[PDB]
Amino acid sequence: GVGISTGTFNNQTEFKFLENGWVEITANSSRLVHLNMPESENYRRVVVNNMDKTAVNGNMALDDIHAQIVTPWSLVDANAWGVWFNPGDWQLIVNTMSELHLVSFEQEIFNVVLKTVSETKVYNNDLTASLMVALDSNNTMPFTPAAMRSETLGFYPWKPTIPTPWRYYFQWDRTLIPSHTGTSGTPTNIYHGTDPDDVQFYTIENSVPVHLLRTGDEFATGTFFFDCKPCRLTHTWQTNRALGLPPFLNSLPQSEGATNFGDIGVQQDKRRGVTQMGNTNYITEATIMRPAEVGYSAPYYSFEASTQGPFKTPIAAGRADGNPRYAFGRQHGQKTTTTGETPERFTYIAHQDTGRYPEGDWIQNINFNLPVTNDNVLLPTDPIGGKTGINYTNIFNTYGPLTALNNVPPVYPNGQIWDKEFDTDLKPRLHVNAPFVCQNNCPGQLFVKVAPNLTNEYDPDASANMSRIVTYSDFWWKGKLVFKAKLRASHTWNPIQQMSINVDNQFNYVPSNIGGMKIVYEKSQLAPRKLY
Amino acid sequence: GVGISTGTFNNQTEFKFLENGWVEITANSSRLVHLNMPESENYRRVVVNNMDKTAVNGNMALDDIHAQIVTPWSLVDANAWGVWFNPGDWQLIVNTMSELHLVSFEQEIFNVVLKTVSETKVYNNDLTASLMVALDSNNTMPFTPAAMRSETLGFYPWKPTIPTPWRYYFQWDRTLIPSHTGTSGTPTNIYHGTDPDDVQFYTIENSVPVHLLRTGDEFATGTFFFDCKPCRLTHTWQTNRALGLPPFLNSLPQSEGATNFGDIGVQQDKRRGVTQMGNTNYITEATIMRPAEVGYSAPYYSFEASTQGPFKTPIAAGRADGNPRYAFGRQHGQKTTTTGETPERFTYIAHQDTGRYPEGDWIQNINFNLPVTNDNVLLPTDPIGGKTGINYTNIFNTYGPLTALNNVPPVYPNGQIWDKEFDTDLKPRLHVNAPFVCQNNCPGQLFVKVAPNLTNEYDPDASANMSRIVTYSDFWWKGKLVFKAKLRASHTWNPIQQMSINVDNQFNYVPSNIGGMKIVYEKSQLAPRKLY
Amino acid sequence: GVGISTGTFNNQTEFKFLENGWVEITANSSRLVHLNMPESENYRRVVVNNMDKTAVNGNMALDDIHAQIVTPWSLVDANAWGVWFNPGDWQLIVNTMSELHLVSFEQEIFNVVLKTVSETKVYNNDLTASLMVALDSNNTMPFTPAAMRSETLGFYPWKPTIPTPWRYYFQWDRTLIPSHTGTSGTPTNIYHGTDPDDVQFYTIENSVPVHLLRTGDEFATGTFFFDCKPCRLTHTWQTNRALGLPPFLNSLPQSEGATNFGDIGVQQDKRRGVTQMGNTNYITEATIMRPAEVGYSAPYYSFEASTQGPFKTPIAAGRADGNPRYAFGRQHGQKTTTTGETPERFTYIAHQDTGRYPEGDWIQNINFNLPVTNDNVLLPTDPIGGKTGINYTNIFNTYGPLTALNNVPPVYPNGQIWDKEFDTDLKPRLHVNAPFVCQNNCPGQLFVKVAPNLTNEYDPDASANMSRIVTYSDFWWKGKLVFKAKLRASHTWNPIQQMSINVDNQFNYVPSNIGGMKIVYEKSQLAPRKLY
């Protein structure tokens, strides 16, 4: 009713230790969401064209041209690690567990309170107004993860959070011929328009049922059950130079110190083994036959153009290319007492050794006369195309049927948790934005809107926008996310790397004297893992 | 007891011909293994740094820098084809069978005899000494196939074989900037050390239970059961130029001879068919649309660098790149009466036609004015980067979603049989060192050590190494490997290629007058196979 | 029999994760023990009198006078943490667990091998000689923990260890009047003898049954079951100044920085609360009434004399007094490749805040005129007895009925595990040498001896010692120690302190190039714990 609560606040993380070494992690996240009324109750088709910056030669990468439908609805996203875990629970997980599954997810919206402003300002209660809630359970509306724009719910359970205004990409065409500082003419930079065979205009009213929650009702999305593969919390260190049986050392050091080394007392052209160079007698560590390849090379800072513009070719694993950079604001980890619109940024350097170092590659003639001449070698310091700053490693792809990679690690607290799978015939082997991927069905999105509050002077035949009573809602969101983890076992004599608190990172986990909080980024895959 | 045998010698290969065309091949292999006591009963951390050879400009491929833990244990490896088959059984298999499965594997160690030397030299029996045996059934210790260093058991049932000293790769860091003969400065060549987050020190005592076998006991590893895909003993010959319906010959030869040819009596710009060149009217054999691609191109003699140095990028299929070179000694096929430390070497040229011929590739402009000019073509004789000895085929990768390949063929007798699967998220499609790959569980490794035989003057608080009685063991190893094969059927009018003995390879299978034996290499995939 | 093994080597640590958050830790420890024959097959009564060092005035603390029975038996002690755990398992325990119980213990002696030396030296096998084993299950013989002399078994599973020769304290009397550098006469320093009412001569032959193990038998002590209280792996930080409700801050900082503080905006003589100073109006943090007292003060470096000499009064908790110092050799953690008889030493600084800081104490008159004069205060800088270097805190005891303490933390790897309880009427509340204490029954001690090997010329009526054949044994010891632990839960927003590997302590867990190992000391009680 009017004076009866419809739910309970719960932001606890429960660890249930089943036997066989399996744990169930139930993460409860409760927030107070504050929502304003839409600036315009109509769907808009907007085109963004930044030719002022791209007409300058050499600024192709600064392209921001697109077309989007702007919607009077807001999205409630909880697809980020920080919504569900604090630094302590994250430490427990990444120090005690080895793998991690994703079992269940459920949401509720309760304790809705709608108010109106009258201008001093007076705030009255609209006991009869309503909040429209929609849940796209069938996944008809386009998927839109907020964690890539850093627009999820806040990371603090005691701070009210806002939802993000919903919008999606409309089709368009765009051609942008690249150039450089010093081109003669004017490269083609035109927004072509829209292809009528690709137009797709979605509406929440025509696709999903909408509930009208007043002050005393409750919305509960039933528990969605995932079916995915487990994310590993252990990293690998073995490249192709550390796979298999090492060479037998005929001379071992006698006075163990700093610069006393061992010696394989056999000439390199008189050693035993297998090699994939069928015209050479040298058996070394760079030449011996390994089972497969750990990682691959890819053209870095390469821009492929398609029917809607240029985009950076994504890289699977990093070494700075391949390392994701996160920028975010005060709701999502930045010091809540800073001033200015400059976001906080960090580059996540993963622990896994699966990337390449292009300054150490080279290609030499098949004759293999081992002291290489200049005409029989291609170095990462040789001009390709006549460009002093472009070498062959920029146009090099070594992805073949022998490549072994690892999935991306969880990024606390700004990374995604789950992700949609592409609705194509041949699916990609991994995403670079989320460790988990919903294969067939993925949790539905939760849209919220505040119902129109009309005045007594409303004319539908008026070109001007309708006149509404200034209304704003605040409700409570609750979510339950259930994981299944395995507890890790020690297989080495030596201890391993763990996450801990020390004198340097001490004040990142406690608030300041003025209530300033922050959530620094923590690494997930700490413990090593034997690859082969 | 002391005078009771604990096992039996069996080195027979049994062929059980079940109906439906399925055969069970039970290979029994018995050897007499001779083991010395460890040179040092401690684990050693050794670093090998060969900067004396790599400080010379142009010798990057001669890198042998690494770090390894040297272990007082020895490994007993039987993962090679020659341990289980002689030339006759191999002929029978590769001439009568079509596919080949891997069913079962089991090992036993029996008839242990431990002796001590007293210095003339007197050899006494230690009836109370013990031999430590460990079996890593859970696969905790790092995998180490010996067939890549040619350190498996011997290939002759009447020759005593030795086990190889066990060791494994310790983590390290290494950067080696490549150069050539004629570089100005000194390229960076430094051994950085070890990253504490990747240190992994394994011990047999802390990971596996150890049995202490005296003179009258017996160790038996239970039968391990594989679950893999069958290796095919038939090769394919069809490239992309021999797929589908040939063109109709309107003029057929009338006087069949040597140089009388047929003629497609239709102009090339007036033929019917499908082509993936949507701007040309020519339909030829180089242009017509084939279902997919058989093979791929890969950058050959390419060296990718990672956190531990440079390594050769492995190639799936060869045509000399892609063809494995095997070097080995007198236990593994070399003439047992040769003198010198020079190993015997051979390059295995496979029968399958899935590689490329870079001297016959080229890339031409999309305009396709068929008599090509110079500015509209890129040949394998054009300098890339200004290097006379490097052309575009060295930096070329044509591996896409349309590539069809074949697994690697068995290499008798020096090739591996089975292999571990990489413990990564995304697994490689094939290994280049073994036809079979254990997907989840793979047979455990068998470590042997001779227990410490202490004297009466032992002080644990002495910095010097302990004083031991010179002890050596000799035991008997038995192994059973069970395959399942299918018998092949003839589908062509013409006979096929078979392996046979002739006047040229006659004395490779019989011993000399001084007892000299040898096992030459034989090819496995002889019979053709229709690909499409 | 002669050529049949009687046991198996097992040095694995198994973690069985039962549900409800309880884990069973089964630690298996296997060693190869080397034993020589006794230097004399008789019991000796020896008196050690070091008057050469104590006759010098001021050297009372260098007293080493005592009387001991030296026994031809050796003790096999496994009461140390390093025998059962390596750094990895210790990291797992002290990072994942909260408490720790002690469930079970069992030992076995197997694979006995006895040999004789003949002098070059020849080592023959005595198939008929025997090894005497005794197990004091009824605890008749005096208890003797070896970990206080650092004489337990070795910490490395791959190094042969020796047992310690057994001996125990015989009664004696001793008076040593203390003095200083500059005393006039000669203080009384005399060894009085033995009181006939306290003589106690124990023998293994008259108290325990002895088994005679030949080459082919096995001794197994049944599983002993403890019943003790759990050791906590969490430390406390709250002293008496951090107990209860803090004072209300009427002025809170507005510009949170480094030196911006809060203010209790109430005068100290106008505050509300309870105080145990019934004649003062001041309510501060040093004066407010706390529930009880956390810790106590004790006279530090105090020497109490009794009927057998002076001894240091033991201290419960440390802050350097109260902090135990461990000295040990190459079997017990020191670098196994060092040279010299200097042992390695470390002082264990515990994490718990329960000690005192005598430089911050003082006693002032009961009148409590707050700005203290000199005649109304006693500072830690005031001479007591006229001695410039002795203040009142040296003779101060604040142990009362309001004192709350914590038990001692486990010390890896040199600390004890369990301990006997004193057989007195009123028992102490805690020991300072072991976290666990056997209340009624404690595991029996395991004595080993090599049986006399007589020659053909033996006369019992000869005053000279018997002539024996030089004999030495080596056997295998196995032990199983079962703990029950609870897995810890996170109750704070901030992470906690964990043990980890880093660039500084990296090479303490991996061996050198010459096989040099070491076990550095690790702290046990890392995570905080709310006391009140």
Image: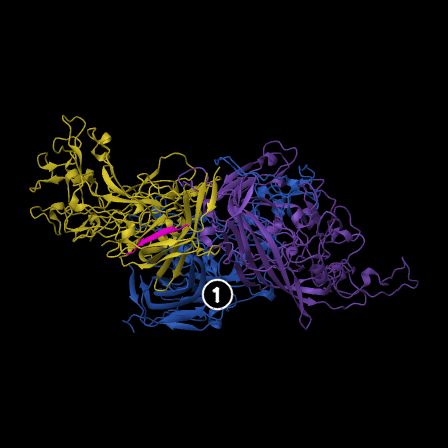
Chain colours: A blue, B purple, C yellow
Q: Nearer the viewer, residue C524 or B322?
A: C524
Task: Tell me residue B11's x, y (percent).
Answer: 64, 59
Task: Tell me residue C510's x, y (percent).
Answer: 45, 44
Q: Chain of mark 1?
A: A
- Residue, x 7% and y 42% (percent of image)? C366
Q: Dot 1: within a 10 Å radius of its alpha carbon, few (fewer than 14), some, or many (20 or more) residues? A: some
Going by the image, does B65 lie left or right of A91?
Answer: right
Going by the image, does B345 lie left or right of C72?
Answer: right
Q: Nearer the viewer, residue B420 or A31?
A: B420
- Indicate the quadrant where residue C358 lies: top left
Does residue C414 belong to the magenta stretch?
A: no
**Does the magenta stretch mainly form a helix, a strand or a loop?**
strand
Name the residue that disc number 1 marks.
A43
Q: Secondary structure at mark 1?
A: loop
Q: Looking at the picture, does residue A35 appear above or below residue C310?
A: below
Q: Nearer the viewer, residue B42 or A514?
A: B42
- Indicate the quadrant where residue C311 lies: top left
From which residue to which does the magenta span run?
Answer: C129-137
Counting every numbered tag in the picture gives: 1
Q: Is residue C232 visible?
A: yes
Task: Tell me residue C287's x, y (percent).
Answer: 14, 46
Q: Is residue A64 visible?
A: no
Q: Amino acid at mark 1?
A: Tyr
- Indicate the quadrant where residue A92 lies: bottom left
